[PDB]
Image 1 (cartoon, rainbow, N blue to C red):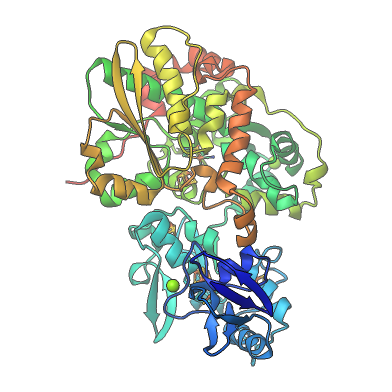
Image 2 (tube, rainbow, N blue to C red):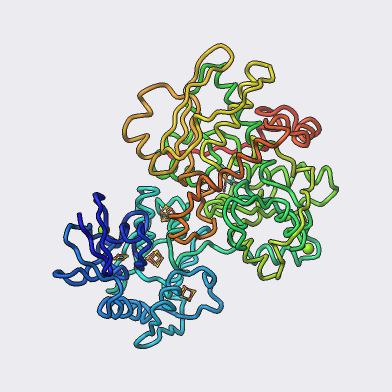
Length: 575
Ligand code: 402
Ligand code: SF4
Ligand code: SF4
Ligand code: SF4
Ligand code: SF4
Ligand code: FES
Ligand SMILES: [Mg+2]
Ligand SMILES: [Mg+2]
């Protein structure tokens, strides 16, 4: 094929779109509604408009290149078309970037600046209450910012296949939202926040917990613990112009101390706990020849998916609490026993790459004697915002260490944030538990990677067992519906709602689609975790000294008695 673009001749054999071919050859073509290899089929944004000689104006993002095409990407007609579309978007957009949470990384603002577009008449809604939905424990909608680009709908479709995010006809105009415009929590929505990640503007956000945290910090009698998820140390640096794949653990500890948190712990400790319980439970099921399979339960998105689509699997879920909740429980029980603090004055805050964690933390039964396991959950973005608001020079901070009591962790706990990490850690402990030995080779590279469905045959003590890692909610649906679950007998199955694992969580920093083309964000974020695992002395959860001390001195033997009674949570289906 011979393609003429802006007077430049190309000879190619590729069968692709104008947009992709142009961007492969460093030709600038703007785009908005195009993301995840699809656009808004109904109301195309037409920001990707180009001029094809003989045909007229076309959308580059969904138009294949053809031999003889003469394309102009920067003609006056094209620019006036694009500018017109952007102006029409501005007509329904509250253009107040000042207090906006996407001010520093908004795509729409970049487009407005680029094409110098102005609204025909500024959209200044006086009461935004009709435009805002904050009923959810995880997600919030601000339709004064919504461009109706459909990116959240497509992302929900491709990531979860639930289509919990839909186009709706409200009042006679189109909005996006949950089924029947209900609160997302009350639908089949997983609260995974992939829709947020896909959003180019501030229309979709996480349910803020920053005020809980601030009020707790400023409350004289409250002792505020903070603990960050595995993924946070591999991600937040992005929001401080430090680049991708940068380990910023120590800087985070320092920043948290400067924020005024009273205790600095780590969720990876909780991960080691979860492994302590779950590996024990797995060995128990192995020696009892059942029941099989056992599913992980640490992902609240997956838990909600099971609740809403496969309740019969609820009794197959591990009873071990997630690292977050198990850490919280221990923070309300064990921690006061080694600190002298009044448990009621303890306020436990987690930092998560996840929006669903907010819902998990606010589950009614996630408490004991009137004390919440977790009192607040802030996302990576929220923590970054809190750091910036405090004018803390994050990139220049010196490394500090976490408080040891519930802050030490192994590499096994460290790799939790990546798909297949929980599986690998769990196997590392379970083999040692079952064989009553301390094995050398602990790396299970078969369960790693971005493959949607991963399988492995592991040999434990005498026999062989089948494990599966489900990478993404849509892949859970595929795994179940295709009957892959019935092809063989599975014994242990990991499920993560977000493809790539928690490193690609709904509470993670937004990334420019261009940088998304430049960088494999999932592998790069996971690389930090695996690198931490490689260079750590202890690489098994049961080799965690602080954790071993905690079990020996307080909880006793895992998987039973005190440990089972306090550190476990069971989901029950309804009759
Ligand atoms: N609880 C918990 Fe987890 C741990 O440890 C996080 O904190 Fe994850 C991450 N990163 C998130 O959110 S949840 C799913 N299990 C894998 S990792
Ligand atoms: S969504 Fe973007 S363009 Fe709209 S107010 Fe916020 S920063 Fe400005
Ligand atoms: S919420 Fe965001 S992603 Fe969804 S249609 Fe509106 S602007 Fe697009
Ligand atoms: S939170 Fe997840 S399941 Fe719910 S609408 Fe958004 S992408 Fe879909
Ligand atoms: S994979 Fe991780 S970030 Fe995504 S919903 Fe599950 S726990 Fe949250
Ligand atoms: S980016 Fe092509 S129609 Fe929206
Ligand atoms: Mg299309
Ligand atoms: Mg305080």
